[PDB]
Image 1 (cartoon, rainbow over the protein chains, first blue to last red):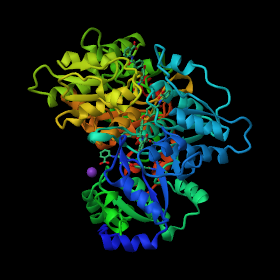
Image 2: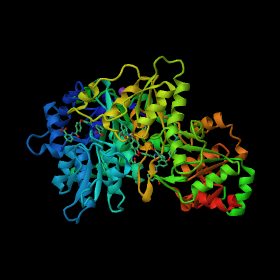
Image 3: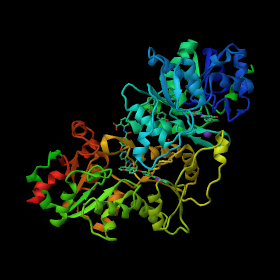
Image 4: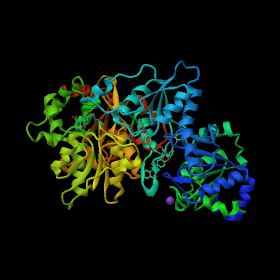
Length: 311
Length: 311
Ligand SMILES: O=C(Nc1ccccc1C(=O)O)c1ccc(Oc2ccc(C(=O)Nc3ccccc3C(=O)O)cc2)cc1
Ligand SMILES: O=C(Nc1ccccc1C(=O)O)c1ccc(Oc2ccc(C(=O)Nc3ccccc3C(=O)O)cc2)cc1
Ligand SMILES: O=C(Nc1ccccc1C(=O)O)c1ccc(Oc2ccc(C(=O)Nc3ccccc3C(=O)O)cc2)cc1
Ligand SMILES: O=C(Nc1ccccc1C(=O)O)c1ccc(Oc2ccc(C(=O)Nc3ccccc3C(=O)O)cc2)cc1
Ligand SMILES: [K+]
């Protein structure tokens, strides 16, 4: 955990020692719809050497198939056909898995999803009916009118994911549903800001999840990184061996901390949000938790692996 | 800080040593439009005894003048006419004063207010123009469209107050405005829940302010209780003497903590949010901050002061 630059020799040693590599799609492989220069060639070379490539993302907007299509379109060489989805693990699919297990044996389970269409679709495939996907503008002169709005009959969970239609009405409805102790609170991810191309960014799902949490005085179960649950899903379907697996990430609090908590080796790409200066601040601090989110190796871009892989 | 019940004897002695009593309007004096039973008579008796009564509230929805009208309407016996407003101190008015200080020397001052009409009105009286009050529904299929929406040219502050129209578009616009370093971030209050009559509650301004804070990675300046600023505003016009002043409140984290930090004596009314068990948790805990939010006296309702006052 010394944030060593992964030079070609160091990279060759690490690559020989690891037969699986896990990546964060946003900020490592690609930004916006534009690939990080050289990243596609790097991942294709890694597949050529026989290394298993897996993808972990905190984005609830896209399904497994959609993310796989993006990776193939941009030349990261995923398997073609339906099998592609198996390679990518995202908060939407993992949220569906969490609700499948937790609400197992519940008849015709339904949930209030303050989230994207893909999240609702993944839940539907799991069998969880979804309500609340879409706009919910506020109507009423005062609080009583807002609290009077009708609610769906059987809602056993609230899923907070990226919802551009998020409103105070949705927050009030979420609180009302969550007043029942049985009702679960699920947060897709806890990212404060999410990066976009050209150094632009938009507010992160975490802002919504913290708003709902505070309003209901409940602590949500966060499916996404850095929670061990997303790693457990990957481990259930990939059979990950922590000693022989690497996590490539751009965000210290989510990706790198996932690696540290789950005993995976960590590579930090500076293409994305986090910076070497942030690592230095965490290193200097005496807090052990801050020390956890310190990467084993750092690369300017994933493309810096190409010299070793082009061997 | 032993949370002793305010018996009639204790009340008479305490009233003898204190010549000013400050109250929280919501949850102590009244809930909704329904007054706490006997409270109007208590405050009227305090006026008759000569005790100076002042009001501090975290609600940005209501103007100073409107709160005064509520006080006379419900029989709490404030001075009639314009001077009524002098008695009430609220987050809207205090926020306007804060912006008067910070935006002093600014031509045509403007702010993006995620808030009520009353908040904008108080700002307007101070001279600060308001933008964004009202619905701003999100339209557009993706992030680029949302960030392309035009913004007003001159915004030197963003004020996050209770906004029933809060939406992701308003959060994005607030983030964009706060990206300029000069732009200030002001939060009217930081309450997670606000109480309503009938034991129901809705989400608080604090949830919205925390969402904006996280999205902008900025620390908002919180005007409302327990911030020292609201007490300074009260003291500017009242000349508060801590030895002779009491704070009557229903919420430990806001009212009682203001009393402790500003060295005012504290009475807890159980009519509102906080409960004796919460006080017990703070007393038992070894955290010093929890010990700060422990009331000196506790009264079931302010009406239990009437026996001492009817003397
Ligand atoms: O919810 C969306 N749509 C709809 C909802 C209801 C009805 C119709 C639609 C309709 O698109 O017709 C939606 C969701 C997302 C949208 O863009 C985004 C694309 C990508 C991301 C993203 O990088 N996400 C993250 C990445 C890293 C870490 C966290 C996140 C996160 O999202 O928390 C975000 C938004 C557009 C429409
Ligand atoms: O989130 C809160 N609770 C919970 C969340 C999950 C589960 C349980 C609870 C549970 O309280 O059982 C929360 C707690 C307390 C809250 O009041 C507050 C009151 C005042 C302030 C405040 O002025 N703070 C600041 C002061 C000055 C400058 C900046 C700030 C700032 O906060 O930035 C904060 C919270 C609210 C929610
Ligand atoms: O009690 C209230 N507050 C608080 C009390 C204690 C602690 C915290 C808060 C706290 O708000 O954080 C309260 C009272 C009344 C409330 O109804 C409201 C209803 C409507 C609006 C509002 O913007 N309305 C409009 C805005 C734009 C355009 C039109 C309108 C309209 O009403 O036509 C605000 C508050 C909420 C909380
Ligand atoms: O608040 C954040 N920022 C700032 C705000 C103001 C000023 C400066 C900063 C500034 O980062 O300089 C913030 C930082 C990092 C954030 O990622 C996080 C991701 C996840 C969690 C988290 O609890 N993850 C959970 C996982 C499992 C179980 C429970 C939780 C839970 O959240 O309950 C915290 C931070 C977010 C905001
Ligand atoms: K960077």
